[PDB]
Image: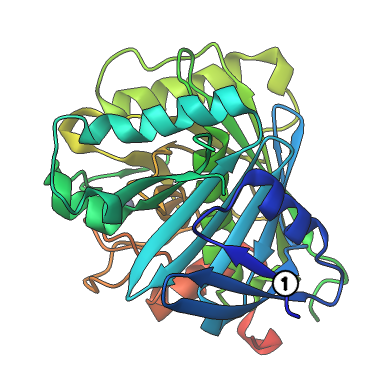
Amino acid sequence: VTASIDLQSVSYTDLATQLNDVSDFGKMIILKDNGFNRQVHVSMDKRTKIQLDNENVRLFNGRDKDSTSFILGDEFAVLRFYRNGESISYIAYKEAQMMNEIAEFYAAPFKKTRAINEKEAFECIYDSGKDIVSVKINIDKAKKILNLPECDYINDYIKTPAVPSEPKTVYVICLRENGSTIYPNEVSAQMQDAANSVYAVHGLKRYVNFHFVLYTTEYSCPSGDAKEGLEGFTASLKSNPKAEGYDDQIYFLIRWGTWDNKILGMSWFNSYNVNTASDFEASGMSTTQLMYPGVMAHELGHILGAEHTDNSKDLMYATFTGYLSHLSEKNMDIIAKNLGWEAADGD
Ligand SMILES: [Zn+2]
């Protein structure tokens, strides 16, 4: 009988035992809910590495037709999949107190809202007896219910100032802003979407493997202004003797919130090229909250040379779309060029 995940009671140990059983050749898992049954073929993501404060975080993919992915650390696990065109995340933390804190955190925006549809946007999942074992979040339904202010990207980038035998490792050094609380499920999802938006372009996993690390920085933005915040962040990287000799990597300042004018992130445009990266120029900033998936991917796009497009299904649309993929062939060419690819190499 095929392994299955019961979405009416899914816990951290459920997800951990299933994903830890995924070998080199993949594993079939059936996702189950009321009137819902989806068989997905799960595989380990060997392209991307993540440590959060030296804690190792592993990624998992479904087939394209599955619209499913996973995240697993020692402390938490994530299942995210699409149903009826809407993303749904199941977020499970191992320790009971941190699960309770996470559940209360995600319940906060609904504390004045009563919809009688609230459970379709946010729901605590209970063990099969009143202990929360995960939370289920549908951010599209949450946005419809909450009718909150919509942040965006307008003016989110400034101007500066034979296939290889092995992909080049590119470190993406993420720095938790001084005073920020970042939850591991949220930042890991942003990193996963960012790396995957690049691999999907011109077969770029042949050329790059991203390695994310997260640490805390003493830097914090001096005002609410994103441009001033990014200028200060890059200056703080050059001032820091710790970072001597890593000026050719990519850097993100991350926070849970946003900046003035509902700005979601900011980056130096067209600032990374595998052959010339230097002087901490490939740097940006990004929110990490769950309601804005793909902001890190969008900013990484700009760093790699991608422009805004007029296609509202594109990751690089000038206002927030929630979509996670590059659709502009013009953007794909410059991203791939800056990562070492040439047309003669094919896809
Ligand atoms: Zn942008």
- Could you tell whether 295 is left or right of 242 in the image? left
Residue 174 image position (x, y, % from top left): 58, 34
- Could you tell whether 137 is left or right of 14 in the image? left
User: What residue appears at the point 53 percent right and 24 percent down from the top-left corner?
Assistant: 176
Residue 110 image position (x, y, % from top left): 22, 36
Above or below for 162 versus 221: below
Residue 14 image position (x, y, % from top left): 68, 53
- Could you tell whether 43 is left or right of 121 in the image? right
User: What residue appears at the point 71 percent right and 46 percent down from the top-left corner?
Assistant: 13
**Amino acid at dot 1:** Ala
- Could you tell whether 88 is left or right of 144 in the image? right
Q: What element carries label 1?
A: loop
Above or below for 48 versus 157: below
User: What residue appears at the point 16 percent right and 34 percent down from the top-left corner?
Assistant: 261
Mark 1 lies on residue: 3
Quarter in which the C terminus is drawn:
bottom right
Its colouring scheme is rainbow
